[PDB]
Length: 121
Length: 128
Image (cartoon, rainbow over all chains, first blue to last red; front, side):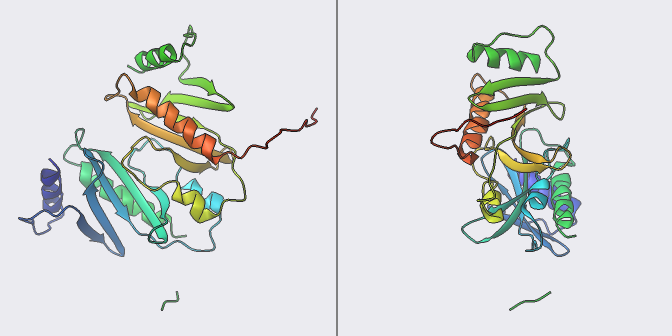
């Protein structure tokens, strides 16, 4: 059912339907590299690694996480292993329809856009 | 199906079943007042307002929100409307079990207990 979900999603996005479906699928939407996988079993998980800013205060960052009427609104978190932010959303694979994966990906990138409101090595 | 959930819950918790069942139900465990409600429709939301500390840094507080295998692991957030922190979890009202609503409340409370910092001995504080 996961393979069917990724297949259907790639179709809707006009993406080359993979004959081989890896555990973690990748889809880039502009500057946001999104990852799609099943975890835990029966749950579709999508995450992106946003680039926050030291300027943001704790309460402001935590404000993004308040619940809303949309269960797909993404959660802003931190991965202590890698040492960087992680924005993610999740939904059940049992209760999934034709616009589901597509909508979850859209909700994730919109949440990522909301986190932005440069120097490099 | 929501009222059917609050009953089984209160029953496993040996609580008095109200006469009206407000859209938002309240259950208090220890020092944590936990609010329960169906939001959005079909989803059972539980939340409590935990006491935090400037001690914890932004990365520490956000690290509590990483995804894991447990979908009931609560989320720490901030409610800018009320101006306070909110810890919450949520699960499909159409997939509950004879141990789900319970495990959800337990996960929320355990999450709040861990964020709390209590004095060894609470001193007497004045007020009006």
